[PDB]
Amino acid sequence: PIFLNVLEAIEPGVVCAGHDNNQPDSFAALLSSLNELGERQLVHVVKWAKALPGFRNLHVDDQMAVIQYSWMGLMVFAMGWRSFTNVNSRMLCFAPDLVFNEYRMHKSRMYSQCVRMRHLSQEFGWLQITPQEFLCMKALLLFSIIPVDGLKNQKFFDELRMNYIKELDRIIACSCSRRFYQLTKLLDSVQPIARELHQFTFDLLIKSHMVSVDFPEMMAEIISVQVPKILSGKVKPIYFHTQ
Ligand SMILES: C[C@]12CCC(=O)C[C@@H]1CC[C@@H]1[C@@H]2CC[C@]2(C)[C@@H](O)CC[C@@H]12
Image 1 (tube, protein in one colour):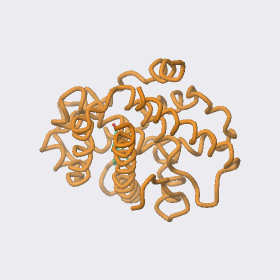
Image 2 (cartoon, protein in one colour; image 1 turned 120 degrees about the vertical axis):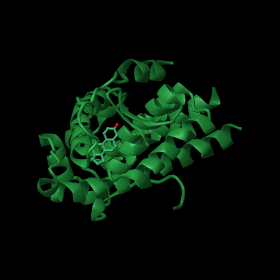
Image 3 (cartoon, helix red, strand yellow; image 1 turned 180 degrees about the horizontal axis):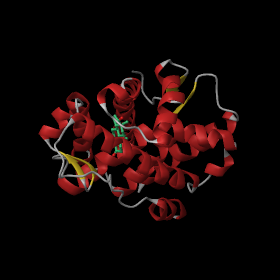
């Protein structure tokens, strides 16, 4: 069980948003706190990804690219699992110091996207996803979004993605076929949610000065440089099933 030992060992711990819960639940304060959480989580996502089995097999340029394409889905999927585990998906647990209730969902101007994130969180309960299945599915999310014109070394990526699909199947083999259908469907469902949030954050970055929303340095870079490749169709999710 080397592979699972590794995924358990490298799993990031708790990250706080730094949100001042004393201030009013305004759009500006909530989204500025979410952006800071994003910057703080990205540090952990990079360190995690670089530690995954096989990741250093990819070209160095491909290593950064897959992180910068996949972070939104990785972070939403992990938040959905934290929300399930902490509060049975009742609220969205972005961080211990930034839990969205109904009011914050409305004030954030993301109510509909939050509804979809809550549905994803609830699937963890409905499907009785185990921690092992969660860890293997989250690793596969890293290898689920790539440029249409290919990566620098596409073959190395294809081999690695194949290996993570095999590991997900092995975890299931510990019926089997039905479970695999369910888990791949759940993985695909993260992508449309990530696309909605990519569009929202891109639009918010462009108008950020007008609405007093702060974007930290790495977030502003990734959202203006890499996110538009996704929104313009140059970088696309790899779906299991026909959409
Ligand atoms: C990835 C984050 C932050 C980390 C997390 O737990 C999930 C969450 C999903 C919404 C994202 C947010 C980062 C900041 C974004 C991108 C905002 O600009 C708009 C939507 C936010």
